[PDB]
Image: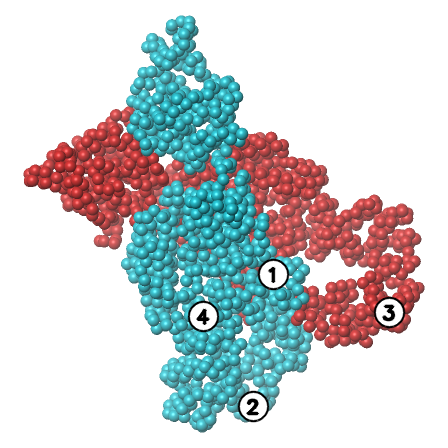
Chain colours: A red, B cyan
Amino acid sequence: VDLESKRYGEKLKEVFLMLDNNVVECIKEITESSRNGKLVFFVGAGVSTLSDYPQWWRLVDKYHEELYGSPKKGNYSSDEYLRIPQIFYNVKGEMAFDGILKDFFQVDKPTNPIHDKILAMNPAHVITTNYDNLIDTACWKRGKYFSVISAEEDVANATSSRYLLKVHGDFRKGFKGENVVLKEDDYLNYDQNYPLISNLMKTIIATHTIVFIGYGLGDYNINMLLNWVRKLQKDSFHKPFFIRTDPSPIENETLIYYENKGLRIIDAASLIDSNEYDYLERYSAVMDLLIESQENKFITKDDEVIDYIYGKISPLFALQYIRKIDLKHVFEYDYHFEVNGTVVRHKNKGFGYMERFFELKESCDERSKLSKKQYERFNALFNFFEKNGVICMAKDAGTLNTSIEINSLAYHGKYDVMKKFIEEQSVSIEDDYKKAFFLACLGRWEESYDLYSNIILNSIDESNGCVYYLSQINRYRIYQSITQAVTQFNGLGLLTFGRHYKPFTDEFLARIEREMTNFNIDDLFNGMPFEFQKKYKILEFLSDNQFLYDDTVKLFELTNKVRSEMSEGSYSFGMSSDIVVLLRLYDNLRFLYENCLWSVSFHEFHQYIRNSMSLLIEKAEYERTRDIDELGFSFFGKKSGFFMEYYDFVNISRHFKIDDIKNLERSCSIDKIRFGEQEKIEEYLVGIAEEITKQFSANGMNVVFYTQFISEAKAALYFAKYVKLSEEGLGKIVKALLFYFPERDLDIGKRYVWLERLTKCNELPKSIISIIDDFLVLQAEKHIDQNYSEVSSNGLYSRDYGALIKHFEKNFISKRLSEITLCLTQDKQKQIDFLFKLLPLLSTNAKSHLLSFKSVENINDLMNGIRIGLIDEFTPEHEELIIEYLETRKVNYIVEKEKGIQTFSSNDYMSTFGIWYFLEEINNSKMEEFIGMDDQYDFFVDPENFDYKKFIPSWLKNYNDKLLGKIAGNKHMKHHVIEVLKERVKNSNDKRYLEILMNYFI
Amino acid sequence: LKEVFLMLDNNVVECIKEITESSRNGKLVFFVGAGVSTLSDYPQWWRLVDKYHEELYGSPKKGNYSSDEYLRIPQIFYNVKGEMAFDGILKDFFQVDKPTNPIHDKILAMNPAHVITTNYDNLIDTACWKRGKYFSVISAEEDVANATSSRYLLKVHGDFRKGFKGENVVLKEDDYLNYDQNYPLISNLMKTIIATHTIVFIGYGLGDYNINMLLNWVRKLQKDSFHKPFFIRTDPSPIENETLIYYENKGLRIIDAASLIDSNEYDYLERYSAVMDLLIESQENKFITKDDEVIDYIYGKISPLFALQYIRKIDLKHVFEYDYHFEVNGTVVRHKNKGFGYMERFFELKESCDERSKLSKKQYERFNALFNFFEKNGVICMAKDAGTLNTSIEINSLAYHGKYDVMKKFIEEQSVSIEDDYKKAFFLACLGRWEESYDLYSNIILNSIDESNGCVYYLSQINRYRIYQSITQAVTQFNGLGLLTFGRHYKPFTDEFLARIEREMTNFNIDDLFNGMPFEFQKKYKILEFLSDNQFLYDDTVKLFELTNKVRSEMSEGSYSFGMSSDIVVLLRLYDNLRFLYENCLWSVSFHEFHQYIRNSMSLLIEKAEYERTRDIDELGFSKSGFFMEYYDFVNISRHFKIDDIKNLERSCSIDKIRFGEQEKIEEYLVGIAEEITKQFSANGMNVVFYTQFISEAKAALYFAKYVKLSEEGLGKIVKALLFYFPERDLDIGKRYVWLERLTKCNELPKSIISIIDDFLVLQAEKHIDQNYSEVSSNGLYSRDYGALIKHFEKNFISKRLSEITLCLTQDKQKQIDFLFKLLPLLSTNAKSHLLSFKSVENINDLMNGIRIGLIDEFTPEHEELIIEYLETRKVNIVEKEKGIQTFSSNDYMSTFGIWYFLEEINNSKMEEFIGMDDQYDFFVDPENFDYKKFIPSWLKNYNDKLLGKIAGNKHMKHHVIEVLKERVKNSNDKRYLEILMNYFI
């Protein structure tokens, strides 16, 4: 029945079952040639009769009609077919011939389905013998582009790589018989008149498998080609195939003779009985057999149910750990794989081979029927499939529990084992390539390039050649890498390096420039063995810089497409299952194709993958803080998802930068984000500590290695505040943090800030304190030279640098520093000032010995003591000393009033003077008679009578030391004061005012 | 080099250009001889023939070996001794190793397509290992069908790689005379290769028999259509002209080495190095030294595609091999150009007409065409001497503006030009989601292949494929949910369309279209590869739109005086998006999964940049950008955003304080959309295929207000769109009320709008009088809200449409008159008196309505006792058994009860006898003991008067009530929380 595979389905399956060996092997060869892109068709004129095109015998009958007046009775002789027009051309002239041709050919007919049927079989080249554009129009409307060749200049002006030859020429240049082979003299002088076309046809016969179609035995062209081919050794010639839809069965003797001639005959009459006029039916039946040959994978006890997949997957065994999504390209999108491991039959027609493969896989029984070789193939394929992580059929879903593991030592950074594995002797070529990739990203790119050259020297012997492609790609990429490396080194100059660390002598630069010049990377795209090209098609995007450039675009689009829903704080229900963040994490962890890569972290644009995916994972806090601003459910615990593991920590340390970490923590609560694996991360941090300790203990030619490892420490240590280190590793991490980091990279201020954050996150009971004291002592002997100074980004203060230690232990005194103080004299004033910084942690004897050095003789020295903290509470003698100056300021205030200006920008001590009186540090009534000098003095000395017309909330920037907390309970007019804050908050967008509106208000 | 090049102007400078062009296209093919072997010091043939002469004749060659003597003399030996002597002699003279000369390496460096070596050797074969190039070697006919790779290394006379025996190589004259018979499969291949490729002879004998046969063949059959080959003459003595002109008439051109350099006779290496170095330049720099260079090397590259009106700025960087950085602003600068500054020359020649006068007339016209093309795209000057490049962005396409009547007018009109047919097809795709004639694209295909214009077939195929995908997606949407969503099985597409499109689109070559297109299409229009594969492809969708992620990370600004608005944020974020709005105004925007969304990622940072510049400087009026959002950006916002997007924008961004430009244009656009939706409500049926998305646009316009002052008529028309013209499925009564309240709330509500609202109420009353229809409000907004909205903004609002119905009521049913019962305060005095006489108020709903509007707030003890009895019924509903009866969200009146408490709307404290079941709302009777998060901040910002002048927290719960508000404002982002904090009390 029509529109159903009845004559196309079961009966053709039975016919294929009863087919002989010759026909089935011809079908297999045809399918192989088609799938290899090495198939060329030879279209005859017979199919033209299927479209009701005018026939040549009709034309010659016409010519005889107007030649002798009456047509010749009976069937015309074959020779006359090429003889009657010639005489007609000799005497009647050209005009009658042209008129008849234009009368009988200026018509158009629709294209028969056989045209597109043969066209939809990826034919590389098509050789025709006709006088129209029926096949041209068919491939035209189908969409395929073919370059029509019918003249010598057409051969000369070649434009594409798909040829549609015209053995006798078309009628593009007019309806003239001179340019179209139609006469016997043309058949005699074809070689002389058209040498180029003939030579091209002879060349194209040998290179491909010629499949004749729409031809009858005895035609002149076929006989001529057979005569040509018989004048050959035929030692390595491929016998062409023939299609012949005769209504009557073929005699066996003729079959034997033509098989001996060198043609393999496929008969359509022997297929099924049909009417003598059903040529279209026979042609369509042949087409349907050769098309159904695709989805003709019948299943038996011993069959291709494992062999087909074995053939499809066998080349891929060379690679270590391929991606799940890439498999969709292997199976020509017959299925669609999921990152979870399920496989769904989408966009598939025919037989579900994957389903039967599964049914064999899970079922222990019903498998002994397979052959032992098939059993081994099944075992190998099952091992490969279980290695990748494909779980089961999409129908048999559930219990989706999977993890991610990486085996490369580069990921974990075991540099000791790294080098240890580096030294040993070579064994084979694969381990040489692996150790060559290992040799890079370590600071010895010279030897890495040399080993890549050595591998590429003798890699053609490889059975698969994938190692050849990978080595070539890595060589190209390392060439660019060293190019930009030397460019950046020239750009930095001596600013970054104390001495310009040239990676290598310019001779190597010259030889690599000569080697790598004019090297456009095409490889598989244009030239590489066709056997490799038909397979391994998933490595086609490797021609770019990174090993995933073309495959990163889908992630770039999909991250936004899924941010369309995972990043919006309006909804508060909370997604239950099929969490998009988990599948995004699975997808990006799948991209850790670390078994076979090159310097993916080096590519600045590659790490953006990590720099964006985890960023959006954290920006998914919109799903958090839900049901807190909304009713929602009863769960009011601010605990988001993303239970990050060791791998997430490693990725954040590897790719995220310190500034980006600050940006993300500006608007997140990772402090509240919980995470497991409290022990492995400690080991990773410790290993980083020994690596940085060994590197900086005796620095050498590690500048190439000292470009990414240095950035690793910044990300690792700063982020480590979130995790809770054990006290045992805290000592090692502090030792690494303090002594062994470079001084230029980290000043005192940043080291102090990071030390403060680790101390706040994890306490320091007794052990780390000794290390801090030792560092303080070492700084003390550093300050021996007065000329010695250090640059601080945020502050050179050592007050807090030691006040932190005093905070840990109130009763703390440094005995070693005490003796250091005791063994000094009044010659090194900078050392005296530094010991002044260290006064709280010094012993009483040290204080007594040091105070004999410097003292307060004037007021300014007394306030200079306030700057350094010499005298926390000065004696009443110093109180009245200020009063004498305050009286001196008082009498000069009248003089300054007469001057017409107020000089309070410098010596702004009255604001400080009123601080102590307001702090109740000084209890005297003398200061009140000096009222009115300064607005700050008014606001502190007499807060109950001051005038707030000054309107200066900007002082709140410097009221951290004012101890606003004490004032908060001591403001005489809190209500008047807060109205300023309300106005300032409304009329200013600064956040400092918002801080005071909280730290010390409501 | 250049010093010698000064005189290289005699059919040499153009020959180098032609050879380099052939190399670029891959048509270049070498043909190496025996000279390179001599450079590698390979054994010479004359030594072998001298040895053979000594073997038989005796004594060395007293005379000289003639041409024939070089061939027949060994053959005679073959006729007197067996092949073992030949094998021994060849082994003695050939079992040697020779170093690979640099000539082989440089020959590989020029990267040819095919190599044809006539000499028997492995030096060139071995040299491929060092470069790594892979070649398939063809020794003879035995290995032809085993074509390993496209690259070929053909051995004309075989080789001694397996040529230990004498039969594997042809050297004797007997083999030469019957060479074709012995090796037929090689001669034809050589002929077709030299016919279909550019062939260059290097280091090759001029008088050799092989070139003799070649020449006697090529000019014998071909006269004028043959491309003349290239030959390199490397001889010490300089060549003369009579032989040269004789060879030119033969059909072969000559490039001698003597003209270039004449260092020494023996320094063949020097001559070969010079002649190859003259080609090493590869036509990448200093190819020509003439003037008027702004007419060549650019015109053939910058204007083969001028049929496309618009070109993106980022595209021109790919056009010129990234030699210049084309900024989004419109300036350029050299990046990788190494030579003459042709762009610099063009910029200099643009203005100075004095030096333009000397330009050739046709060259002048081409220069003016290039100038017009550049100024149309937006390139005006160079980054070296240019400042700001802020320019108004405009669109010429009518689809992006929203015109529809002229759209139909053009659709009715026929189109003759192929471009006009493309425009018509695009416009039809705009009007109808599925083209009733997608065969218009087939006509585009056939006409484009008919014509020689090109670059129309390629685009139309992509458009057709995208249309196919969209139609299949529409079919998927029209699943079982589609039938109920649209009311019934509409099935706009019929089955035969699917049947034909599935059979046409099957096995489509979406992998790549450049393979189908010839080489010239791929090379010239390489700029179309951005959307060619379009299989989630790059640099057309997100690759430059992923750059905004970096700015998203660069959002953080130090201190307070930085600015994300008065900055370069317009560069690469605003102008980049505006440039990428249309690439050619004809590409199908039909796909909406990514583009319309990523349009809301844009216009998002810009909106967040509207922080009123309060932190940029002290005064919010910074006084520049201005950010007057003109109508194009308004269209973007009202086209690509959703309801919830704009909702969360209004949550924590400036909305009303921002002013938009082109307000009259916005008025025109809104009036047009309202008029066309009203017409289409009557013009046709659902036409869901266009309706489904289009209504979204309408919605995005209605709730986007408080921006323009609507004209009296237009507002009257736009509110008329709400007069039962919008489908009630999308907008119920509650949503209509909300959007109506949002509109005009900043206006004074003229009397025409009041009459329109009264008419709406009249139609709703007619619907209610049906006695069967029941009001449907998802948000609980009853029809009385319109009555509450009116008369609360105006006075003396009274209508004669419905009061007469109340007076002339037949006292039939209360259900159909519940609308009038609720609207009692708006009713006429006599009518309301009659209605009051007809129906009293006793039910809890009646009491709620009476307190809400009309009647009286305080009530008799029996009424509050009835409310207590309702509370007792809620007490019984004890029988909940945790089966959903405990949920009380559907009936929202328990909280309303507590609203009367704490507001002195009670006569006794009997509610204390009923413990509040609503855990959300119970603290009104037990303020001291409240459940954790009893008060949800959403409910906190809901009401406005229960603060009652801040006494809500002043009477009790003074402290630990601002903690929740403050932590909400600290973590979340809402202005309402800040205002609640400002009043300091709940």
Say whether mark 3 and mark 2 are on the same chain: no
The reply to whether dot 1 and dot 3 touch (C-beta < 8 Å) is: no
> Of tags 4 and 2, which is closer to the observer?
4
Looking at the rendered image, the quarter that the C terminus of chain B falls into is bottom right
Please, what is the three-letter code of the amino acid marked with disc 4?
Glu
Which residue matches tag 2?
A: B858
Q: Is residue A563 above or below residue B3?
A: below
Which residue matches tag 1?
A: B566
Q: CA distance from mark 4 to mark 3?
A: 69 Å
Q: Chain of mark 3?
A: A
**Sequence-wise first label, 2 or 1:** 1
Say whether mark 2 and mark 4 are on the same chain: yes
Q: Secondary structure at mark 1?
A: loop
**Sequence-wise first label, 4 or 2:** 4
Q: Is residue B44 above or below residue A116?
A: above
Identify the residue at horizontal 60%, vertical 61% (top origin).
Answer: B566
Please, what is the three-letter code of the amino acid marked with disc 2?
Glu
Q: CA distance from mark 2 to mark 3?
A: 73 Å
Say whether mark 3 and mark 1 are on the same chain: no
Q: Is residue B407 above or below residue B736?
A: above
Which disc, if any, is residue A898? 3
Please, what is the three-letter code of the amino acid marked with disc 1?
Ser
Q: Badge 2, how many Cα within 10 Å: few under 14, some, many 20+?
A: some
Q: Chain of mark 2?
A: B
Q: Badge 4, how many Cα within 10 Å: few under 14, some, many 20+?
A: some
Q: CA distance from mark 1 to mark 4?
A: 30 Å
Q: CA distance from mark 2 to mark 1?
A: 58 Å
Q: Secondary structure at mark 3?
A: helix
